[PDB]
Length: 304
Ligand code: SF4
Ligand SMILES: [Cl-]
Ligand SMILES: [Cl-]
Ligand SMILES: [Cl-]
Ligand SMILES: [N+]
Image (cartoon, rainbow, N blue to C red; front, side):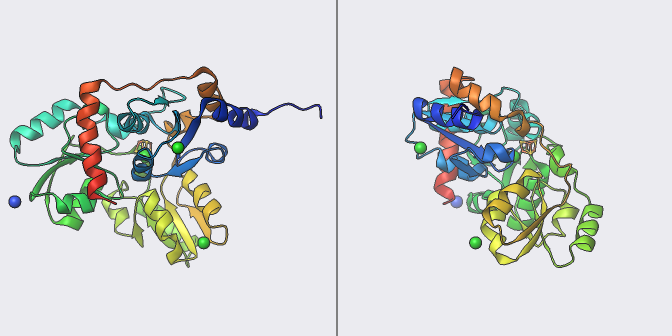
């Protein structure tokens, strides 16, 4: 035939030529999800990054996630297709916040959401994600923990563990999940009265209280078998992921306008260019990386 390769075919060929794997987050565009080798939540992506046989990891996600993969694979090439793929919640937490909390509470473990910079993780005793934060905090040997950046996840952790949670910083949150209100809950239940509600713990507490299940996107996938019809209170591309996994169920976005600009910095074109040009190479300074790796490997040990 006369036709040549499209972007998908170019990517497939370059993945072979580079001995590369494409890891994608659940909030990636559908056409990016469709070319990824593995798709998951933050914990699943971290765990998957400990069994990489490929030489090159193309990370269809935000920079903190790519940095986590690099911390776990210092001697592989990790590529981020755009350096503008970044997380507003993670940027809210600075070293100065951690140091001030450690001064007040020197005996409190420092528990940092993976939505955090590599520099911040160097100060964590253990990292967490939305999937394992309750379990990890429960098991730590202290009734007081320093926790951040996300204050809404911190609220959920405090509720479920009964422990004293010292937030760092004071107001960390995700603007995507802050879009959900009690009015969205009322509207969803009126439009879909037989559906149950899957709610991310980055949503505000009063919205969390309306959930049938509170879960990371990975937990949403794991527990979707419990009902046939769900309203999805997270970033709207998760609806595509759930529909692909469970074509026989029904999924509805809680809000179509719950979009993460940083996630959508990743495009099919810039994944192609990432493999073609071997860019942008993610690097983490050795001293930071070694300290962060200790905290991440502790997380993986404490949460299977
Ligand atoms: S959805 Fe929220 S927490 Fe996740 S990368 Fe985007 S801004 Fe960060
Ligand atoms: Cl692999
Ligand atoms: Cl996220
Ligand atoms: Cl199934
Ligand atoms: N102890």
